[PDB]
Image: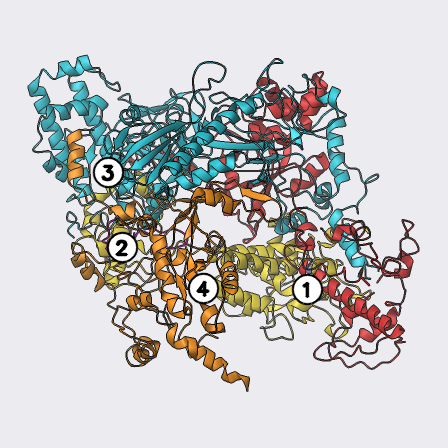
């Protein structure tokens, strides 16, 4: 065609978001800072291990992480177990890190761990097969279901209908109350409760549920269909098998006993808690955010990085039309799994830091004009 | 006929769009259901039916010939009216434009996009439960078979009341009129709309076959059936295709209601089946177009003589009319047919199945024993 | 009403904004249009759409390609399989591996980048990577490259910023007999331009269990597989495998039997007959002290294995030199470390360390693992699905010649015949404005071509295009005519190009290709039927609404009666073409005829198809008599009847129309395997299923 | 009810009646297990296992006590007194090796296999162990008739009612828009080259001087390659059917509810284009099953005999013409398609002649 016509089309065209068209998994995973070379997965591990530092005994200390050499990786993969070195020849993106704990100096044996090594365009090969890792739309704060209210925690997954987790019964209610008051003070969850629930301890959270969140059971203000104000986590569901091992390792020093340890029990517990495939064994069998790549094309904007999953699709009414669907999602795009058009990624949305979905300004008048025309009956 | 090929272009759209009676029905129209479905749609439905207006246009000539539907043309050349949500909730303000002049407002197009959302709720449980319903109906309907042409010559004529709604179900049926021998209805009688007419049904005629019927008892539907064809399965098939087409208001509730009536104990056990046929007829024919010759077979398949002596066999006179449950019919009769239904091991450890009683014969009996002649 | 005004931006439509007239089509068909995108392969002939919106410029900037992630400098440039002169002079280098050092950083991290010959994500569908000729010449061991300098672009990305997702075809709307149940009557010359590419990979092993065979050569050479850049045989057998025996050496280990292929007692690999070999990868265990393969068969294997071992040895030597130079300060990317441990897995272990046991997803290899990757071009004949970027999709049911296609009175030849009556049923009217307005466009572009001295339906040369431009008044009148046509069609594009510098170049770029590319975004102040009535009720800008001549099913030149308009439409090919077919006269049995493994040793599938379910045998018991419907199951569940039907097929003078195959006097009823198994399992319980009067 | 003493004296095989009676697992698990193993009153008389067992009478029952506390059945005593011989003989049979399937890195076994406890074995303890083994026999046979027979994947509903037939094919469908007959099928080259292999072998051993190995190589070589000899042999094999139009075959639909889902056609033409892999069907037969061109794969079986082709005449394209709902009405499957009707609409319903007033004036 005419080059001036394509120039005028390029001059009058809204540009897509470069962070979402290239993949937000590229941004929120393996993005090195200019100060030092540390990926965002290693930063998430470093921010997860210091939370459970108050559950550690005196002298025990987690001391960063270091990148492993491939000469160490080849010996750690092909480890002789039964006089046979089983090398798995398969194209798989992985990289190996360490843990490097210490107990009053004299640091112990390092525990290597594998990491999935994502690539550009939300694409990763595992065990020969290609896969796509999509982010999950997660609301900031608490979730309001049709019956009860749900809060996310690092170790408990309880709902709220008179139910909690679980002569000689006097020590069970004491061992529960021991861990109930200090282990539920995770700092990242205190930064997650910035929606107005400003608590310090869980005993104030149970009070503020009863005096402020008590009307969220029958006359809640949550619209239950709006996609505004979300976190868009991709790393919270990817490391779900590693956080479980972190919580089970933190249960050793607090829930079981609080006595003096030695290096022979600490090395045994470190070998029994952190194996080689902690975050790798349940990646392609239970994680609903990882899908099989079946795109016979060259563009990644069609089915590569334009897939979103809800909070119910990650586990492997609410389908009311909302005016926020046309802003952050893609309406008139109805697959078989999500026929309402809720799981879709529109590139023309405003996303700031840490995946926080913020609203725009140029389309706000049309959305406010169309929203009040919906819910009037 | 190769020179006369129908075509479609922009000119065929502009020929029907530029009519003044169509353009008058799209301007000065209040957004009301009466103002759209009765006022706006009527002024274009009265000009689509005019045979002296559009001569040569392929769309109108295909509409009058039964190819194109008029329900899909009122949503394009006239005002589209009130698309719905996932649930059956209508909206207050409808869409102004149609499909020729497209929808270009965000609110109206977002309502219109929810009209195609209900066309994807195609979960596998529905296709599983309709196949389970077909397997439950046909396995018990397959007992009666091998109708014979002729006349069994019985005077045990039953009597049924005929109404307006079930008159199509009595199309091919022989009845007894005054000063006459036999006559078939064929469905053109405005009279006999409230009386109780004496018919000739399968309940109570005498044929020498233990599981067969005659042509005059079944009606005029038997000559449309081929000679080597099971009359037992085709009743459940003729029910099930209309049920699946109703599946594809709350047709699953209708399917479970027909399951509870036919293959359960939800019906009150009447003394005679002549009062069980019109209730099932007025329950079925009000929503599913089904002939009563199939309903007679579906009722006769649950009939057992001498229930106090465990003689699980079909009686040839239908005047007895003793009905029991569906599972007792599946287990205590024709074990070769019992191996085809669920819970195969329960007829095995039963003391009633180890004694030689005279019983019926399922067609599956040859597949169980491998294909032996005796 | 306000039919002209509209407020919908491109920011609110995710994938719906790729085509205009989105409000005219239905919601379900508009969703099926987005569903059809993402199932489309890349054909060889790609071109831009005639009605370009503002969306295709944004989808062309985010594709799968080989780009530099950061400002860096190239350190080393390696390549597998070096091409020179001699006996080891294999051509068509598939991949090149380059290593860079990340410039402008506090820690100089080292990275790696592979440039392959192709890229494929689907199992049997992929596209080639054409290389940028400017960047590929500047590939040096001392060269600084900036961020996002693309290498090896795809075929859909053109020189300017566009995206080719389909082919423009002259679609005629006729009620032909071939257009039954969404049927397409495609031209033979149009299907040559819609030709997808399939990249496949076949892998085999040959060790102590079995060894190779001698194809692709005479009795003075041994070649178990074709070389890189060779053609596969007319039969699809590639690296057929024969079992390992000792006492059958003068019978099977002879140069006559190594050349011929036995279809039974062997394991071959069937692929595509006409296809070029692209890549070859050979793994080898070289630590066993007995060599299982005989001599004279391991030349072409080691010819690739030595080059691959030298490549991986240099790849490990570079990392070892970088580790010896920069001690305790090396930073590496997450792709390079996997490449180094892969190079360590390929290279053999020393004698002081135990040897490796290589596995491929719980499948061990035995001393050889050869995988080839080949490329074929698939020509569509039947059961190919197509879509005009709307809800209306179809399947090609009849392929006519180029001379038997519908042609109008202006010489335009049709490429597709689609039934028009399905438009009013499914309510997809966006195909009406695309077929119509383009018919008002090309007939304009063929008018301004024929108004001067030129020839229509033919690309003009430079000597004529440089001689037409001498008349400035004629090109000014043509520019005014094009501006009037744009004012009729698209007022935003017309107001854009009202201030156009050097307007003779617009006339040149219109008369070069024979179509004016019309820009039509999603926010247009256009009354569509008013523009239709302006195009119809006018002397100029009117399409040729005349008669159309064609050829019917018989041999006759047929001219239609009604005036038929032919217009352009942008078509594409879809997924699920006809290749998953099966045919089996005999299937292997269980030690009861079910097989589920890597079944690629026969052309097409050889598995038994469960055509007789429970409902199928119920309908065959009711409609067909219960007698003859048990013989169909007894000819399968009994192996003696399965041998007897082949004996009756092979002993009769007529293979078809045989009266009796399995007589019930020698092989009677009662020899079924699951029936006897159930009878035995019930006999050990203590009861029996019989009857007596 | 089968006499267990009648089956163990008329065996005349290996006559190894002592399986557990002689072996004692003294270095015999490597030999007796892999080479050999790799009327039960407890089935019927099992209404007494709620929280107490009425079968605590261990040994020497001498069943003559009519103490029956049961409300479900009253003819159980008549069933006992009809054939009193029930679990009386000493020779109980052992299930065969085909019922238990045993490889790879890990030995995989199935959970209903719990009958190997009887192969591994004072009188008051041995007599209790015999009834322990008899209760294990009943617990094995009940769970094997419940989990391997009563389930929908099982011996009864999957293998006893037919599965995976031979001489079959499965492919997508197209239409024939031609002057043809209502029962004509067009098999492609790749399907017809493998469905008719022994027919081509017979024709190549009859018309040419070839062995069966060279004939098999000529058949398997020309599957993805067109040649004139295989096409001429296909035309000869079509022309060999003297009273029929070709080879009789059956054609199915995967949802099979109505009569039209299972039809019988005749193979009449093998296609020459190797790229076309689809079976082309008649236009008028498209309506009786719900079959469209939406990428669906449909099944086909080949009738070998003349008697089988005559017996398959009960399912024909002419059998579903008459409706099964109305007594005198042809069903709607005879109705023509859209573009077939529209040409007759444009031809007949046209302003062709002046009206009757102008015609006679
Ligand atoms: Zn009768």
Q: Give the crowd class for mark 4: few <14, some 14-19, many >=20 residues within 10 Å.
A: few
Q: Which residue is tagged 4?
A: B250
Quarter containing ligand 1?
Answer: bottom right
Quarter of the figure with residue C62 = top left
Comparing labels 4 and 3, the label whose residue is closer to the camera: 3
Element on which disc 3 rests: helix
Same chain? Circles 2 and 4: no
Hue of chain C? cyan
Chain letter corresponding to the colour red: D
* Chain-order first, disc 1 or disc 4: 4
Q: CA distance from mark 4 to mark 3?
A: 48 Å
Chain letter corresponding to the colour yellow: B
The numbered disc on residue A328 is 2
Chain letter of disc 4 in the image: B
Q: Which residue is tagged 3?
A: C57
Q: Give the vertical position of D310 relative to C688 (above or below).
A: above
Q: Give the crowd class for mark 3: few <14, some 14-19, many >=20 residues within 10 Å.
A: some
Q: Residue A352 colored magenta? A: yes
């Amino acid at each position: 065609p005419d080059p001036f016509l394509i120039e005028k089309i390029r001059e009058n065209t809204p540009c897509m978001n470069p962070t979402l068209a290239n993949g937000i998994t590229v941004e929120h995973t393996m993005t090195r800072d200019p100060n030092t070379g540390v990926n965002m997965t290693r930063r998430y591990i470093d921010s997860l291990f210091d939370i459970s530092s108050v559950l550690f005994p005196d002298g025990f200390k987690y001391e960063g992480n270091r990148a492993c050499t491939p000469l160490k990786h080849f010996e750690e993969i092909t480890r002789e177990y039964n006089a046979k070195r089983i090398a798995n020849i398969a194209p798989t993106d992985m990289y190996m890190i360490d843990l490097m704990f210490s107990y009053k100096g004299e640091m112990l044996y390092p525990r290597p761990m594998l990491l999935p090594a994502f690539k550009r365009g939300n694409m990763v090969t595992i065990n020969g097969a290609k896969y796509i890792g999509s982010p999950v739309l997660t609301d900031v704060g608490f979730s309001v279901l049709n019956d009860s209210i749900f809060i996310p925690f690092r170790r408990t997954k309880l709902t709220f209908k008179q139910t909690d987790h679980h002569g000689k019964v006097e020590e069970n209610i004491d061992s529960h109350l021991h861990s109930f008051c200090n282990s539920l003070d995770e700092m990242t969850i205190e930064e997650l409760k910035t929606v107005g629930v400003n608590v310090s301890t869980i005993w104030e959270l149970l009070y503020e549920i009863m005096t402020s969140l008590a009307h969220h059971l029958y006359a809640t203000d949550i619209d239950e269909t709006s996609m505004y104000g979300k976190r868009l986590t991709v790393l919270h569901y990817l490391m779900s098998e590693f956080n479980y091992a972190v919580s089970m390792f933190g249960y050793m020093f607090q829930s079981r006993r609080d006595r003096e340890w030695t290096v022979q029990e600490l090395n045994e517990g470190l070998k029994r808690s952190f194996k080689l495939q902690t975050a790798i064994k349940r990646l392609t069998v239970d994680h609903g955010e990882l899908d099989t790549m079946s795109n016979p094309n060259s563009s990644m904007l069609i089915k590569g990085t334009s897939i979103l999953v809800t909070q119910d699709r990650a586990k492997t009414s609410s389908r009311i039309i909302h005016a926020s669907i046309a802003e952050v999602g893609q309406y008139k795009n109805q697959p078989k799994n999500n026929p309402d058009g809720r799981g879709r990624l529109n590139m023309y949305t405003k996303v700031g830091p840490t995946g926080l979905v913020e609203r725009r300004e140029e389309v706000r008048e049309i959305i406010d004009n169309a929203q009040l025309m919906f819910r009037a009956k | 006929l190769s020179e006369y090929l129908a075509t479609l272009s922009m000119f065929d759209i502009a020929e029907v769009y530029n009519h003044p009676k169509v353009r008058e029905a799209n301007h000065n129209i209040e957004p009301t259901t009466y103002g759209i479905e009765k006022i706006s749609y009527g002024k274009v439905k009265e000009v689509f039916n005019d045979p002296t207006q559009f001569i040569g246009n392929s769309i109108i000539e295909g509409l009058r010939s039964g190819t194109q539907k008029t329900e899909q043309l009122l949503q394009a050349f006239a005002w589209r009216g009130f698309p719905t949500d996932i649930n059956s909730d209508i909206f207050k303000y409808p869409v102004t434009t149609g499909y020729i002049d497209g929808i270009w407002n965000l609110y109206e197009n977002m309502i219109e996009s929810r009209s195609g959302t209900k066309a994807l709720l195609y979960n596998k449980e529905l296709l599983r439960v309709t196949e389970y319903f077909n397997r439950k109906s046909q396995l018990i309907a397959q007992y009666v078979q091998r109708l014979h042409p002729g006349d069994c010559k019985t005077t045990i004529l039953a009597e049924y009341p005929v109404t307006k709604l079930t008159l199509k179900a009595f199309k091919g049926k022989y009845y007894q009129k005054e000063d006459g021998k036999l006559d078939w209805i064929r469905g053109n009688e405005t009279h006999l709309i409230g009386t109780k007419q004496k018919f000739r049904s399968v309940f109570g005629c005498n044929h020498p076959d233990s599981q067969g019927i005659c042509m005059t008892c079944y009606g005029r539907l038997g000559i449309n059936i081929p000679k080597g064809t099971n009359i037992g399965q085709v009743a459940a098939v003729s029910m099930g295709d209309k049920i699946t087409s109703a599946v594809l208001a709350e047709a699953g509730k209708l399917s479970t209601e027909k399951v509870g009536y036919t293959s359960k104990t939800y019906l009150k056990n009447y003394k005679s089946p002549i009062e069980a046929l019109p209730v099932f007829a007025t329950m079925a024919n009000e929503k599913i177009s089904l002939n009563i010759s199939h309903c007679e077979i579906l009722i006769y398949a649950m009939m057992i003589r001498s229930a106090q002596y465990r003689d699980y066999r079909l009686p040839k006179p239908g005047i007895n009319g003793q009905f029991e449950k569906y599972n007792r019919l599946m287990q205590c009769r024709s074990l070769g047919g019992a191996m085809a239904f669920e819970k195969q091991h329960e007829p095995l450890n039963n003391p009633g199945s180890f004694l030689n009683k005279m019983r019926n014969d399922h067609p599956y009996d040859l597949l169980v024993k491998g294909g032996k002649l005796r | 009403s306000q039919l002209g005004r509209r407020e919908i931006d491109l920011t609110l439509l995710g994938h719906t904004g790729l085509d205009p007239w989105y409000g005219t089509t239905s919601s379900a068909r508009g969703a099926m249009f987005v569903t059809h995108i993402g199932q489309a392969p890349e054909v060889n002939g790609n071109e831009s759409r005639y009605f370009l919106t503002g969306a295709e410029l944004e989808y062309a900037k985010y594709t799968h390609d080989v780009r530099f992630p950061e400002d860096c400098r190239v350190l080393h440039v390696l390549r597998k399989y070096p091409t020179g002169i001699g006996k080891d002079s294999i051509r068509s280098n598939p991949v090149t591996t380059i290593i860079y050092e990340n410039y402008f950083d506090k820690y100089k991290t080292i990275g790696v980048l592979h440039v392959p010959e192709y890229m494929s994500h689907h199992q049997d569908f992929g596209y080639e990577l054409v290389k940028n000729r400017e960047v590929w010449e500047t590939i040096a061991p001392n060269e600084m490259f900036s961020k996002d300098t693309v290498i090896a672009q795809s075929g859909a990305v053109k020189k300017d910023g566009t995206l080719g997702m389909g082919v423009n075809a002259n679609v005629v709307f006729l009620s032909a007999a071939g257009t039954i149940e969404d049927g397409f009557v495609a031209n033979k010359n149009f299907l040559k331009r819609m030709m997808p590419t399939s990249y496949s990979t076949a892998v085999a092993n040959a060790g102590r269990k079995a060894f190779f065979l001698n194809m692709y050569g005479d009795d003075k050479i041994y070649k178990p597989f074709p070389d890189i850049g060779d053609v596969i045989r007319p039969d699809g057998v590639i690296f057929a495998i024969r079992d390992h025996d000792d006492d059958l050496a003068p019978a099977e280990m002879t140069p006559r039997a190594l050349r011929t292929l036995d279809r039974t007692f062997d394991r071959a690999v069937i692929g595509t007959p006409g296809a070029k070999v692209i890549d070859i990868d050979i793994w080898r265990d070289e630590r066993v002290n007995p060599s299982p393969t005989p001599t004279g068969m391991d030349a072409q294997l080691v010819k690739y294995h030595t080059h691959l071992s030298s490549y991986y040895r240099e790849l490990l030597k570079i990392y070892r030199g970088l580790l010896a130079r920069r001690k305790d300060d090396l930073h590496i990317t997450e792709e390079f470390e996997r490449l180094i441990v892969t190079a360590q897995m390929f290279l053999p272990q020393p004698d002081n360390v135990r040897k490796l046991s290589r596995f491929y997803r719980l499948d061990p290899l035995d001393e050889w693992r050869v995988e080839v990757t080949y490329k074929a071009q698939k020509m569509p004949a039947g059961a190919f699905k197509m879509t005009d970027f709307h809800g209306g999709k179809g399947v090609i049911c009849k392929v006519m010649e180029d001379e038997d296609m519908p042609i109008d009175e202006n010489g335009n030849r049709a490429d597709l015949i689609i039934f028009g009556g399905s438009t009013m049923r499914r309510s997809n009217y966006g195909r009406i404005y695309e077929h119509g307005f383009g018919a008002a466009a090309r007939d304009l572009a063929q008018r301004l071509r024929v108004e001067a001295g030129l020839d229509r339906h033919a690309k003009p040369t430079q000597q004529q295009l440089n001689s037409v431009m001498g008349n400035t008044q004629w090109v000014d009148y043509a520019f005014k005519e094009l501006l009037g046509f744009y004012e009729i069609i698209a007022p935003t594009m017309h107001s854009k190009m009202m201030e156009h510098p050097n307007p003779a170049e617009h006339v040149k770029t219109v008369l070069m290709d024979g179509f004016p590319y019309i820009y039509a975004p999603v926010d247009d102040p256009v009354d569509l039927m008013a523009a239709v009535n302006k195009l119809i009720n006018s002397d100029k800008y009117r399409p040729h609404y005349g008669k159309v001549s064609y050829r019917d099913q018989a041999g006759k030149w047929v001219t239609t009666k009604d005036n038929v308009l032919m217009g352009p439409l942008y078509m594409m090919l879809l997924e699920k073409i006809g290749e998953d077919w099966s045919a089996a006269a005999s299937v292997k049995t269980q030690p009861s005829k079910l097989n589920n493994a890597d079944r690629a040793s026969t052309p097409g599938r050889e598995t038994a198809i469960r055509s007789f379910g429970e409902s199928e045998t119920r309908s065959y018991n009711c409609t067909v008599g219960p007698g003859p419907t048990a013989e169909i199951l007894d000819q399968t569940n009994n192996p003696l009847a399965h041998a007897a039907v082949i004996e009756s097929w092979l002993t009769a003078e007529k293979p078809s129309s045989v009266p009796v195959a399995v007589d019930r006097e020698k092989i009677p009823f009662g020899g079924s395997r699951p029936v006897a198994m159930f009878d035995h399992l019930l006999e050990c319980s203590g009861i029996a299923l019989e009857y007596a009067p | 009810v089968v006499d267990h003493n009648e089956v163990h004296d008329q065996f005349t095989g290996k006559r190894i009646y002592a399986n557990d009676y002689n072996t004692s697992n003294s270095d015999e698990k490597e030999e007796f297990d892999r080479h050999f193993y790799s009327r039960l009153l407890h089935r019927g008389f099992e209404r007494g296992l709620n929280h107490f067992i009425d079968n605590f009478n261990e040994i020497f029952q001498f069943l003559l006590d009519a103490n029956i506390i049961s409300n479900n059945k009253s003819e159980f005593a008549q069933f006992v007194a009809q054939n009193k011989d029930k679990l009386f003989p000493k020779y109980l049979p052992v299930p065969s090796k085909l019922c238990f399937v045993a490889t790879t890195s890990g030995t995989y076994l199935d959970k209903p296999i719990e009958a190997a406890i009887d192969a591994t074995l004072s009188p008051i303890k041995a007599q209790n162990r015999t009834m322990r083994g008899l209760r294990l026999y009943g617990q094995f046979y009940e769970i094997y008739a419940k989990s391997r027979i009563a389930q929908k994947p099982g011996l009864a509903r999957r293998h006893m009612f037919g599965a995976r037939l031979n001489a079959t094919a499965r492919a997508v469908i197209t239409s024939i828009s031609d002057p043809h007959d209502y029962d004509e099928l067009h098999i492609p080259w790749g399907v017809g080259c493998q469905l008719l292999k022994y027919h081509l072998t017979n024709k190549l051993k009859a018309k040419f001087n070839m062995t069966t190995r060279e004939a098999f190589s000529f058949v398997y070589e020309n599957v993805l390659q067109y040649n004139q000899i295989i096409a001429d042999l296909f035309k000869e094999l079509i022309a060999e059917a003297a009273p029929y139009k070709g080879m009789g075959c059956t054609f199915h639909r995967n949802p099979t509810l109505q009569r039209g889902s299972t039809q019988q056609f005749f193979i009449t033409k093998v296609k020459d284009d190797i790229n076309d892999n689809s079976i082309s069907m008649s236009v008028l037969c498209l309506k009786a099953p719900n079959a469209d061109f939406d990428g669906d794969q449909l099944n086909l079986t080949l009738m070998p005999d003349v008697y089988l082709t005559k017996a398959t005449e009960r399912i024909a394209p002419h059998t579903w013409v008459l409706s099964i709902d109305e007594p005198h009405e042809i069903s709607g499957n005879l109705e023509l398609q859209g573009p077939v009707v529209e040409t007759i609409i444009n031809w007949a319903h046209e302003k062709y002649l002046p009206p009757l007033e102008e015609w006679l004036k």
